[PDB]
Amino acid sequence: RDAQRMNILAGRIIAETVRSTLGPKGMDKMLVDDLGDVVVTNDGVTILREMSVEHPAAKMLIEVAKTQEKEVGDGTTTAVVVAGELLRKAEELLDQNVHPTIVVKGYQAAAQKAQELLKTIACEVGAQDKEILTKIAMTSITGKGAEKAKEKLAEIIVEAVSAVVDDEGKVDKDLIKIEKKSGASIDDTELIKGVLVDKERVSAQMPKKVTDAKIALLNCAIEIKETETDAEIRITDPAKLMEFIEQEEKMLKDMVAEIKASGANVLFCQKGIDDLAQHYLAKEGIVAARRVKKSDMEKLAKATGANVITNIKDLSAQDLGDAGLVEERKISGDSMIFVEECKHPKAVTMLIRGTTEHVIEEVARAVDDAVGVVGCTIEDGRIVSGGGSTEVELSMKLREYAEGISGREQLAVRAFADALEVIPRTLAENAGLDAIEILVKVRAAHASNGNKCAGLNVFTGAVEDMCENGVVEPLRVKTQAIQSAAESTEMLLRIDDVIAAEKLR
């Protein structure tokens, strides 16, 4: 009957499911499917994918949320929490004989004006500074649950983003690898200036450590090839399989011998090998490997300047790797292969450690997002204090700007400004303090000539300088989040009917 009303009421149900998950403190509400896999995660976008939807219009708010992650990588819940607030204020005006179009024009006028205010509040920082980059690092890691040694993990991530700053001044998400492996604890994390493979030596007869060795990385299986033309083989004497073993050992011995003549020694195969074959090759001091991930063949090619080879016969000296120090040291119990190259490393890799698979995965979801928010701010060079202090300042200036606009439209620009007061309200409930009792003091700091940073601290619980505490965020996350929220709400306001079309493709 109402149709339009069914949308604004439905929009408030999806927001409440991911409203209390804002900020560090905040429980979660899991919805196990019919299968029974009980999974829990402190994230918003991760729950929208598994969680289904009833009405078809509900997918409109989920589509815009996907773009916020692939582009920015943080703040998806910050855009949906402010969306539901607008839908709750719209009905307050529609009952007063107001047309929906009058509310849409108000958000567009306030959204465009907010773009000019955020640029003035944002401060200027350096692109080579380190102390400023250490504060932003502690803000992203806090969003995953890891305060046992955050001071240490924040010191290794700030050095990685600074060592991957090309001359042109950009950031790439490919030259920063990640490897998870639980063993001792999280304190065993270290920044490696190269790559790392989770393999070991196929045999103990080969050398244990070498120096200045020409690595030869292969990628195939020593087998008989076949041309495009059909060619079948016939067999009739089963007593030939035994004779083929003796004829195969010499084929592999002379083959590996040709690789040693070119100055190489280290090898990387892709399948098993005879037990006795490696004996003749290990006594001569020839390192080798078997079964390696294809993803590792790409990073080793750039780290050691090597290149993937498909035919062992076609191998040149230029395609051989050049490592400065290759050693297979231990890492608390288990051992792995390692390669160093501090002379001029082009990439880096973070080795995550822990006691189980549940703790290493938490910190793993923070290193990939930290380099993103920290890699973009270096290109633009503009940041602003977080903690909702930006919305508290604009909440006062938007009221003065509303006086300039006359008519029946000023009721919309005021509702949008007051709608931004939900961010500091949700964080108050989780902290255990009355929001209305603290929301009156924050406005006192931003009276007129006061500072533009006082907000709220979930730890101590009082208005304090957020800059000294280290609570800042990029500037693109705010402009992009507010831009997506202001554009997504228009999809539900500019509609008042649902035709029952069949077979539309």
Image: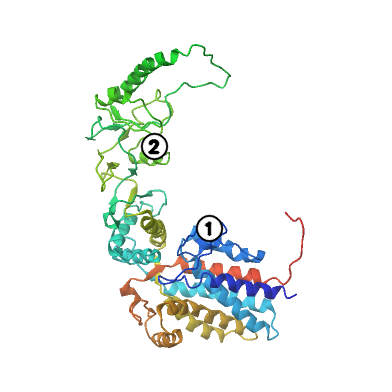
Q: Secondary structure at mark 1?
A: loop
Task: First in sequence, mark 1 or 2: give its number.
Answer: 1
Viewer-nearest residue: 28 or 106: 28
Q: Are marks 1 and 2 in contact (CB under 8 Å)?
A: no
What's the distance in space between the residues labelled 1 and 2, CA to CA?
A: 35 Å
Quarter holding residue 496: bottom right
Image point 77% across, 58% down: which residue? 502
Asked if residue 387 is positioned above or below residue 30 in the image, the reply reads: below
Tell me how the rendering is colored: rainbow
The C terminus sits in image quarter: bottom right
Relative to residue 40, is residue 87 drawn left or right?
right
Mark 1 lies on residue: 36
Q: Secondary structure at mark 2?
A: loop
Quarter holding residue 437: bottom left
Residue 130 point in image, percent of width and height: 29, 62
Quarter holding residue 303: top left
Mark 2 lies on residue: 292
Image point 77% across, 61% down: which residue? 501
The amino acid beneath tag 1 is Gly
Asked if residue 163 is positioned above or below residue 454 in the image, the reply reads: above
- Mark 2 packing: few (<14 Cα in 10 Å), some, or many (20+)? some
Asked if residue 163 is positioned above or below residue 84 in the image, the reply reads: above
Residue 44 - label: none
Viewer-nearest residue: 434 or 383: 434
The amino acid beneath tag 2 is Val
- Mark 1 packing: few (<14 Cα in 10 Å), some, or many (20+)? few
